[PDB]
Amino acid sequence: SLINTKIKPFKNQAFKNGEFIEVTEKDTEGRWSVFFFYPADFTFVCPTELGDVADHYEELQKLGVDVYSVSTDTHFTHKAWHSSSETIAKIKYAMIGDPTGALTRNFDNMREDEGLADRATFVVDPQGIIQAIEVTAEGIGRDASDLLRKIKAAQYVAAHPG
Amino acid sequence: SLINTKIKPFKNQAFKNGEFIEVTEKDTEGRWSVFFFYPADFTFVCPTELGDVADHYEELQKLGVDVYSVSTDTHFTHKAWHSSSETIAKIKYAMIGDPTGALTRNFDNMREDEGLADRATFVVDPQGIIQAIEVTAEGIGRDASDLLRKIKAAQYVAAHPG
Amino acid sequence: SLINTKIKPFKNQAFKNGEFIEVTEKDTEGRWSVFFFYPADFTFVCPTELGDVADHYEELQKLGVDVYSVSTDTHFTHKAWHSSSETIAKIKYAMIGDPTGALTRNFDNMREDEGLADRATFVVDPQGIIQAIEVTAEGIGRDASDLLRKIKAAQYVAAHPG
Amino acid sequence: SLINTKIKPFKNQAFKNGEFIEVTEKDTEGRWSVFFFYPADFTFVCPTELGDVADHYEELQKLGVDVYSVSTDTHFTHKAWHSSSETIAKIKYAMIGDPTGALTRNFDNMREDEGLADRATFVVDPQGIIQAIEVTAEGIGRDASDLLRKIKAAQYVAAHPG
Amino acid sequence: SLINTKIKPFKNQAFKNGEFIEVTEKDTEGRWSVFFFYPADFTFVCPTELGDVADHYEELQKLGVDVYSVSTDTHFTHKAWHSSSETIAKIKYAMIGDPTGALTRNFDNMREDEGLADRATFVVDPQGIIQAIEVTAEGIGRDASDLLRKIKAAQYVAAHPG
Amino acid sequence: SLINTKIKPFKNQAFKNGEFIEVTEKDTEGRWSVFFFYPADFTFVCPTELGDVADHYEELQKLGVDVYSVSTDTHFTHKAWHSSSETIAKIKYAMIGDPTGALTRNFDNMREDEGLADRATFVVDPQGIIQAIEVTAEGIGRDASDLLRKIKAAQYVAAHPG
Amino acid sequence: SLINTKIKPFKNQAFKNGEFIEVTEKDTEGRWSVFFFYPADFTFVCPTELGDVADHYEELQKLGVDVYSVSTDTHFTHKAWHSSSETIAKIKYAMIGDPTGALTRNFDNMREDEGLADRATFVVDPQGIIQAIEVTAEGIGRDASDLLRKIKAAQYVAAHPG
Amino acid sequence: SLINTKIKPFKNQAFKNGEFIEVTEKDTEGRWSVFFFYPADFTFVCPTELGDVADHYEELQKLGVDVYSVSTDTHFTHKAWHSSSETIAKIKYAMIGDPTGALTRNFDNMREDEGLADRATFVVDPQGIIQAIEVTAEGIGRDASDLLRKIKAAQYVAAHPG
Amino acid sequence: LINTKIKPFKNQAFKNGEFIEVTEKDTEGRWSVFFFYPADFTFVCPTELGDVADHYEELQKLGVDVYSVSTDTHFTHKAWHSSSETIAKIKYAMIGDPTGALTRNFDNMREDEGLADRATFVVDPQGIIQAIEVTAEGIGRDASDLLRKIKAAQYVAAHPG
Amino acid sequence: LINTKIKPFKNQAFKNGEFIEVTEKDTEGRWSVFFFYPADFTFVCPTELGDVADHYEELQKLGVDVYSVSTDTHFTHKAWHSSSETIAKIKYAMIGDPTGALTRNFDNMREDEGLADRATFVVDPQGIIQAIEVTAEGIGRDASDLLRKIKAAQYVAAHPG
């Protein structure tokens, strides 16, 4: 699958704490990154998954992990949504917009018939190698705590080969 | 160009004051239709172009003309925008979501670069034949009156062939 | 569509009050241009659409805008029409002949069925980028004022990007 | 070449004595037809060639020959030209318009780089078989009297095989 | 992705509590299934992941869940391993051999250059639809507890749409 | 058409007043040329057409015009015919044999199913440009007088552009 | 090689003692045939070859062997050559004319760059099978007596197989 | 047949008396090699074949003949099988593991629908040429003594050509 | 080609003084050994061919059959059989394959020489290739190892599992 | 193939007791007769081959050369030459063509039999095919008519026009 492969290049606008930033594969370099994809902003689904992440952001920032949530929504939408849902408001990590689906497709995570990304979370090590993958159907939640457990395990393994 | 061609079939989710509805080309047969494409919801630009159309919904509706505004945003976002923006709130016409970009592409009006539609308006007669096309860049705005003048001309030209 | 694309190179014969001239895309570089396509010369329809443009040549010329009307008629016919019709006589802008239909086809505006161009107008900025497209069927006419409004908007949008 | 081959189908609007008629291969059936192509109406070339034909029309109509002059000009133009040049005014035969070049191309007589027909005259017998062909460069005239001489010879041969 | 897609047909031999049986896609029809893939039998990594799952085999069984561990080893090798390791001896669920690697490739889970399946688990509903995916690199264990949670969650979402 | 196009390279053997020579496109460079094609030597049709041209061979010679009669017969056959017929014996111009049929096909003048050239004459200027074409079916003679007229006319138009 | 292959269908005009006839593969069915190809009529080379065959034609006809000399000249030229040469005059067998070159090509015997057939003789049996395929370059003659020997030899082998 | 062809490059892991090693075509260059393929480790069939080869391995090593038994099982399984079977235990030659199936396919010896190699032995000389390609179906055994005879015979022919 | 079914073929050949035709049908319902070699009448020793000769009466009693094959015609085999004493011992069909079709069916052609490689194929009653044996020049085939494979093949056919 | 230049080739063959290699170069600068036949050792009469034998000393005195060809190997030709009395008279090179390349160069292959058709080709010193003669079985080639064509070909080479 995509496991154990290096992420592909990319150029996306995002929303992070009030300001609009731009992101590329360059920023992922040397760092541990988590790409958290979800289908769409402003739906009626519980914004709970993204909240769990936000709730563990401080703990992740401590581990030296960057988080990018991704939807095929424009970064503009992320802004308006970040100031509507009280859950979303808690988000301090970058909220990437992928209206061209290019980032989503780089990760083979596009629901082609919907123009929306699937619920998938990727863990990329400092070298750009995808080390953990998780995808679920609408409705099956992703545990932010299991995500942490794996980020730690990944790093331990990166340092204790064999 | 698409001038004088029949519209390709489609099926998209829409927001029509309160209710989500499914629109297809089947809904357009028999009526005069107007497809008002635009870049995106929740942008910092002026929702003027869309609001103005609402200002004439009275007349248009009188003229047996329906209005389908289209963006590659999901109908979920349209709803959250409709009831979060003054001008957007005036809209009583169906607000189509085209996250797959298929409707947009049938109208050859996609910024493959951004994943957003361009500022374009289409007049479709009851037979589904495009009678008028209008496309402008960011900044040059569309004029609601000019649109109505055309629709009237279009309706008239139909009455007295050649 | 051709919106936001650069015009393809061309070389056609034209009539400009008295003189026959050769126009190319080289003539359009640096200026704002307007390509006014129409079906044919000597038709029993109303030369109104063309005459009106002349009515605004004053201003347009002020705005540093040139006008190239185009039909798949030869420049010979344009001359015989210019000095045989009142309204046509007001024309001080270059009248292009496109008997090969190449210019028309670069603008994807040909009725392959008839060998005549469709009622379409194009606004091209100094870089050769189409900024506004307008196409209507027989009967629905184009409005000279609306055209000027766009050109002004187009010129302005250029001045203060985004 | 095209000699001795049957003409291909066609549908063209024409101008004949004030009224606009339509022509097809059907009308050529059972009759002797002469397709007289020329480049363009309203030029500065001497309209003399078409005049010679007109001058012998009565004599040809007596022989049971139909004449169709053809230019890639619209039948509309033929009308306005028939009432401008005093020579053209003499024309009693149908003046076909071939703005789609389809008729011109059926006879392999299109100057593709110009969108105009070449100076060619074809003689089609009652069965649709091309029996005489003549093409000349701009400037070399066609003798209407030689055309007659050949139409007669054609018919004599049609009746005196071997 | 493979999320929300239907598992493909397959036919493999497996070892299940002392005996050899055949398993196909038809045995999963109507039940919930877990496809647990690992690289190889008899390696030196701790068989903790497969032990975890054995410990919960009763929970999953009460829940109408079938477990299938999969490696590209033969079923003969599984039978043997089931006797070497005390951990592997707890396993009561079916151990599928996949030497042809077809079942593994169906799940796009093959490390092609090693001919071994990656560490990936798939939760499949009674309709053969993949509702959850989990894949990790060597060293990053998979918790049988998190899998149970996700399974209950999937069973819940299938019986409480909203 | 072939009108106004350049003749192609060719190399054939010919009979010219008692001797055999070679003719190529290089012998036409710088001169006016007439390529007179006929179906076959020794048939029963009257050799009037080739006699006509012989009668005017002096006119054409004074005018700087070369005559080349062409058939798909060999040059040996031409030499012989030049003795059978009294008419053919008048011929002083070159008689080209074209058994390979290449010269004939260059002029797109081959009756493929008979392997004989059609009755066609080509007038070529000193630059190798075809200025006049004449083709007739069997029985319809070609007048050497009309050919002279056209030639003078061509020579005139080349030295009096307008 | 064409040895041992069935001759192909053909239809040519020929000159046989006084008049013109049509020969096809049908005429050869049931008989033994000699197809005698030669380059050209009226050349300067003595018709010894054709004459020797002529001398043995009574014998050949006894053996039930039909003869067809072939060249790319027309039957017209054969007639003229026949009634103008001592040797050719003796010929009482059909002289096929092959100006389209099809028959010559059927026997793959064309000198393409000359448009003339090569000096080749083919013996064809009643079933249409080529049994002797003597071919020689210019200058290397053929012997009628040797031809007769081969025909007798072939006729014998057909009577006494193996 | 692969007889008389050079073996292809490969790189596999193997189990050779106690530890794991890497074997490539390089290791075979300059030596005589026996590639002994078999379906699978731990199956129920007695390892008589592998054991007989083991019995004659001292003799084979005298003759300078290297042995590599191969199966699609991993080297891990070979180790476990080796230290768990009387017969397998005797083996002192390298036991190659071919889970990707590449080596097996190199020798076109794969039972594709089973993912297991067929029972085939290949004798390869110092230059890499296959000199004896014994292959048998399941049940049809192989004799080590006969293998030794062939190797001696092959070694002789290399010393005494022709 | 191991475990595949032989293809259809039609060649001329020789068998004890007379000419016959051999097709897959002759192998249909029978057991067979297709023994390919490069060429009749060469300076190389017909050892292999004489070898297979001796066990022929025995193979025949097993309903088993032998067909030697080369790209020489059947006519040449008849000549060789009545000239080389080793070859004269042959009582099995000597197939001629001048078009190379039979040889290529078994993917056993040296394209650069128009000759078949030294290769033995054991085909069961259902036409499946089981005991295949191919060796380079100078490496001999033990008419004894072949027989062992044939009996093994028959035993497995009769006693699966 | 009339009036075309022969192609390059490399085959093994026999010539008076020993083996040699023949290529187009051997024909380069020489005159040649390529005489194809179906097969050595068949029941058909080697009449044609014995025929060409007799004029060989004569052809040789004309710097002319003869190469008989079949898809049999050179080894088989050596056997046939030392077995058939007719064949024993042969002193010209007997080319072996088991791959069929030489035969196919001259477009003279019976693909369905892997054997060359009965066909004679006369090739001049520049390698151009002039006197080509091909006949079906039973129709003989007159070693006399061939010679006549060879001399005619030499005469024309020496005296154009």
Image (cartoon, coloured by chain):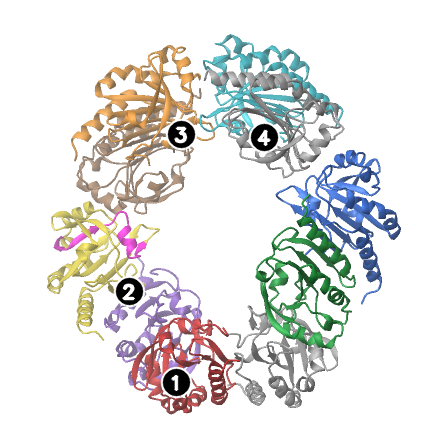
Chain colours: A orange, B cyan, D blue, E brown, F green, H yellow, I purple, J red
Measured as percent of width and height from the top left, residue B14 is found at: 53, 20
Q: Are marks 2 and 4 on the same chain?
A: no
State which quarter of the image contains the N terminus of chain B. top right
The answer to whether marks 2 and 1 sit on the same chain is no
Label drawn at residue B9: 4
Task: Please report contact status of discs 2 and 4: CB closer than 8 Å, yes or no.
Answer: no
Location of mark 1 (residue): J63
Q: Say what amino acid the circle numbered 2 marks.
A: Ile
Identify residue type, mark 4. Pro
Query: Which mark is drawn over residue A102?
Result: 3
The amino acid on which the numbered mark 1 sits, given as a three-letter code, is Gly
Check residue H3 in the rendering and tell me which mark sits there, or answer none.
2
Q: Does H109 appear in magenta? A: yes
Magenta range is H89-110
Return the chain for callout 4. B
Pick whichever, I80 or F37, lies toward us: F37
